[PDB]
RNA sequence: CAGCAGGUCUCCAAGGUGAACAGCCUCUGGCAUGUUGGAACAAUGUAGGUAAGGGAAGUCGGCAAGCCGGAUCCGUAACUU
RNA sequence: UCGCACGCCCGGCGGCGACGACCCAUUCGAACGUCUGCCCUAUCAACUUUCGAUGGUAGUCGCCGUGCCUACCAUGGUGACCACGGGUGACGGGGAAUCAGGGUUCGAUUCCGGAGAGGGAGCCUGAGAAACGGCUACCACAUCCAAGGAAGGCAGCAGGCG
RNA sequence: GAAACUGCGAAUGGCUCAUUAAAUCAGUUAUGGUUCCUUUGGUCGCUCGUACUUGGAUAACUGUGGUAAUUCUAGAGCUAA
């Protein structure tokens, strides 16, 4: 079922080994007026790199992006189309800085084309410094 | 070869040169802080037990 | 008359016997015969060789 | 003042010996040994400490394609010192020198034999280690 | 010209090692070492080997001898039909 | 621990400091991080990956967060929105010159931030160095020498040679 | 009060741009993911178990010098933090 990794998988805050006679879970609000999702509380998973149920806090900047790849485990790759004006030739240039953000399995139905706001945090790997905060649905296509 | 002997009870020291390898056979092949019977150093050195500590070579 | 201890075996080498070996970087090794000479040139550790003195200093044999 | 005290010589004409100095040369092709009168079908051989005529095969091109005098400083053949010790240096080495005994180079890699030092005092000046 | 190391068309093909009906050892089957034996181990020989250091300087000529060599994983140039 | 005036009771009580200290805040910072901005090249179109390249689990080091490093899981990550590679008489910026305007060229040069003392490699002390008018090796250079050995880094100040 | 033992600085400054093409560098940011010499604001009888000051080693100095050569070094007599 769960805890298929090498060591024991649990939240560092919780403790269930006290003398008995559902498992307790610890979470946190994120700030800047973003809600806490329902399944991060309801679920039984753990993730130390999640800004809701892990030892990481969002600080600095908060930006957005659109998902283009998901072929990794527990993280995705986003696309960031931004426009830059050139002073000499008075026209715009199409540039993007695609980079990976850590998608926790707190969200389940994540598809292509979804706009996802993202928050700066401490570096958790070589190049990722971001985590998925909340996921908005795509333009239509409910089915 | 010179012998810069020293006497810690009074604090005096003198330098004596010896031009005989037969005189120096009892000193050779001895390490730091070794009691060496120095009764073969001469006629008037009888019963002297001396401690060898080493000095400088022919280059300094 | 300087008897001096073999580099591989550890036996005393009398001045009329033995063989002198000095590698390129600058250090000198001493061999009593070609029996000890052939082992050192092929990277053989004396501590794994039973008949040397260093085996007896490692296994605490004799004495 | 200093004699030769003949040693075991095992580097004939045609041997390539490595350069143990900083002239930029790598190897030395022995072409002839200076001082050997010769014998019918006997190849002129050189031991350590003999002035020898060499030629660079690979290395700096301004030293190649010409004849250089050399002095052997290391050899593979085991030779007998007068006190009765048999010495070899796991390689054959030589340095580039002129007729007076002055090095073209300035530094020596590896040891130099003791009998090479006293016949050639200038070679011993830049020798890092002896024997 | 012979009980001549030559030549002469075919059937069957054990076990092990090993890709193999290759080379080596063994079983069934066959034999006394191939027109004789004994005693020593001289030179020169024929057939095998080994050599410190150099590595073709030998020789018309790398002749002979010597090096590599099986398998697995990489890697593999110029040229070209 | 030390130094300077000096007092109160009938041996006991007190002053002004310096110095260094266990720890929390200040300052100068330092390093790790985010977004955006860089010259040319297709006669560089596919690049990178068990020789961490891309994420996860668990560890080591570290001042801590991290494939910074280690064993196992997935073969991914990037590129025609020009990736990778190569060259750059490329340290960068604030800025300087010419200019209607739009720009172009220069920017090592007194300010800021980065690098370095011939080259990399390694290091003690010291809060702070991988220092170099500090060390340990090698390479290139190179000084004295009695031949046994010692000793050096002006892309600093002036100055000498090429 | 020479010199010496002991602290701080010598990681500041001056020179140059070899190297370097999202790398340095320039603008907004965070250490909620760490240190911090010196300076300043504070705790510095909070602990429950010879003090009227403990111990023994050294440099300077006296003396031997070794060397061709150095900001090279030791033996004997000490003494202070």
Image (cartoon, coloured by chain):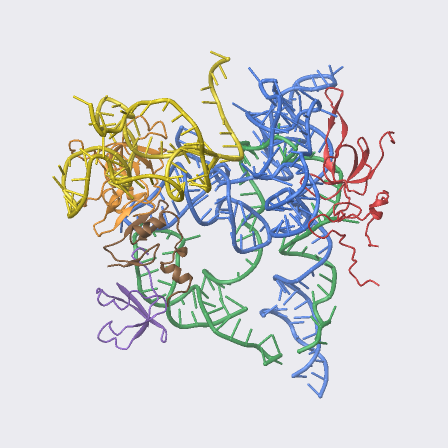
Chain colours: A red, B purple, C brown, D orange, E yellow, F blue, G green
Q: In the rendering, at what x and y percent does residue D121 appear?
A: 25, 43
Report whether G19 appears left or right of A46: left
User: In this view of the protein, can residue A120 be seen by the observer?
Assistant: yes
Against B30, residue F36 (above or below) is: above
Q: In the rendering, at what x and y percent does residue E59 appear?
A: 21, 25
Report whether G8 appears left or right of E4: right
Query: At x 74% / y 51%, what residue is drawn?
Result: A9
Image quarter of the N terminus of chain C = bottom left
Report whether G30 appears left or right of G80: right
Image quarter of the C terminus of chain C = bottom left
Q: In the rendering, at what x and y percent does residue G75 appear?
A: 37, 67
Which image quarter: residue F92? top right
Q: Nearer the viewer, residue F120 or F50?
A: F50
Against A130, residue G71 (above or below) is: below
Which image quarter: residue F21? bottom right
Against D111, residue A136 (above or below) is: above
Q: In the rendering, at what x and y percent does residue C30 appear?
A: 31, 53
Q: Nearer the viewer, residue D130 or F24?
A: D130
Query: At x 36% / y 60%, what residue is drawn?
Result: C53
Against B31, residue A118 (above or below) is: above
Q: Nearer the viewer, residue A14 or G46?
A: A14
């Amino acid at each position: 079922d769960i805890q298929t990794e090498r060591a024991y998988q649990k939240q560092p805050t919780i403790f269930q080994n006290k003398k008995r006679v559902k498992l307790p879970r610890y979470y946190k609000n994120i700030g800047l007026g973003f809600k806490t999702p329902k399944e991060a509380i309801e679920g039984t998973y753990i993730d130390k790199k999640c800004p809701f149920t892990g030892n990481v806090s969002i600080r600095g900047r908060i930006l957005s992006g659109v998902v283009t790849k998901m072929k990794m485990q527990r993280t995705i790759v986003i696309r960031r189309d931004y426009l830059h004006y050139i002073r000499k030739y008075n026209r715009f240039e199409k540039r993007h800085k695609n980079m990976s953000v850590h998608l926790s399995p707190c969200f389940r139905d994540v598809q292509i084309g979804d706009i996802v706001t993202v928050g700066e945090c401490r570096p958790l790997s070589k190049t990722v410094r971001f985590n998925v905060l909340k996921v908005t649905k795509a333009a239509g296509t409910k089915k | 070869m010179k012998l810069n002997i020293s006497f810690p009870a009074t604090g005096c020291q003198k330098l004596i040169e010896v031009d005989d390898e037969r005189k120096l056979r009892t000193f050779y092949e001895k390490r730091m802080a070794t009691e060496v019977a120095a009764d073969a150093l001469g006629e008037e050195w009888k019963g002297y037990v001396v401690r060898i500590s080493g000095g400088n070579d022919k280059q300094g | 008359m300087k008897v001096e201890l073999c580099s591989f075996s550890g036996y005393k080498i009398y001045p009329g016997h033995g063989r002198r070996y000095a590698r390129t970087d600058g250090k000198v090794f001493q061999f009593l015969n070609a029996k000890c000479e052939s082992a050192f040139l092929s990277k053989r550790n004396p501590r794994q060789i039973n008949w040397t003195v260093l085996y007896r200093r490692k296994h605490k044999k004799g004495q | 003042s200093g004699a030769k005290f003949r040693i075991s010589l095992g580097l004939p004409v045609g041997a390539v010996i490595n350069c143990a100095d900083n002239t930029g040369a790598k190897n030395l092709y022995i072409i002839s040994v200076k001082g050997i009168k010769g014998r019918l079908n006997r190849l002129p051989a050189a031991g350590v400490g003999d002035m020898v005529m060499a030629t660079v095969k690979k290395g700096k091109p301004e030293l190649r394609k010409k004849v250089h005098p050399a002095v052997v400083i290391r050899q593979r053949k085991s030779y007998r010192r007068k006190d009765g010790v048999f010495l070899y240096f796991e390689d054959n080495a030589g340095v580039i020198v002129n007729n007076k005994g002055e090095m073209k180079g300035s530094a020596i890699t590896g040891p130099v034999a003791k009998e090479c030092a006293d016949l050639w005092p200038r070679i011993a000046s830049n020798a890092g280690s002896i024997a």
